[PDB]
Length: 338
Ligand SMILES: COc1ccc(OC2CN(c3ncnc4c3c(CC(C)C)nn4C)C2)cc1
Ligand SMILES: [Mg+2]
Ligand SMILES: [Zn+2]
Image (cartoon, rainbow, N blue to C red; front, side):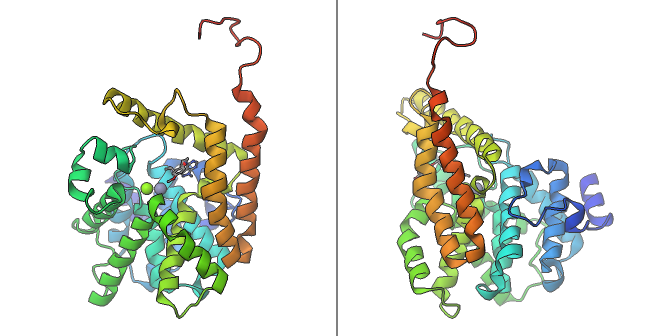
């Protein structure tokens, strides 16, 4: 409750006072100490004018932000620092790409809130694991699909329905319904299976050109932007890409270990005895990440640098690939590992 006191009474720090490069695509939000992230969320909301536009109650917003942060567990990748960095990228898209020409204010607001909430209570395992392990989440959502994403949305709703945390309780009934419906679609769009299903519709929209008067184009654009925020760790330098691969594979291999112990054969990328990290990262960059930022570049010319950084990071994997072969003897001069 002392974090809350300071967050409410100390005042909202200007965005520049965090870092002079905070609003740039070159900035790495993971460099920000975890203890300064809740204040950074308030600074970003204030800078986007959401607090004033929607007359958000300060005690309510302060409680909401801390409740969202508390709602994340500590697996190697799907933790609060992932949600914070994804939310930071949404802010970057707002600051650098002129979203206001494409989306409604409420849609841009829903995107940011969804970014903060999109992986709430993640346990470090994927959708297939929920079903295979017969988890409570699969009992609740397996028949509807996107098990984890349905849970993240339900966790966001449970936070909003906690006394003193409903940042939208003063909204009109229509605006309240709209907001929760947007959060549903945006959070469900974080399932990469959903992205791969709509990819041809995203290509078609970029091809014909975005139509601001087409409601389906608004829905498709919000899906693309959310996916762009979720994979944004790949738009920085090699240092971020390398570190993120360590976190992702530590999480994946922990799942694979659980599947093996259950008598199940894990997917290749989740099996520490079979996974070849450079090949898997090249495949993910080439077939998932690069086409996303290419679509983003096609719709927004100012997003060109993002695609170029992703392409550069993909090329760095090919460059370091030879290091994954043990040439000579290991550092200890022993072949005991055999
Ligand atoms: C349905 O087809 C698929 C799904 C996943 C797949 O690649 C895995 C995802 N992996 C990633 N690798 C590096 N940076 C990543 C990710 C992700 C998503 C993960 C946290 C889940 N986000 N970021 C920033 C490697 C290949 C194909
Ligand atoms: Mg997710
Ligand atoms: Zn995520």
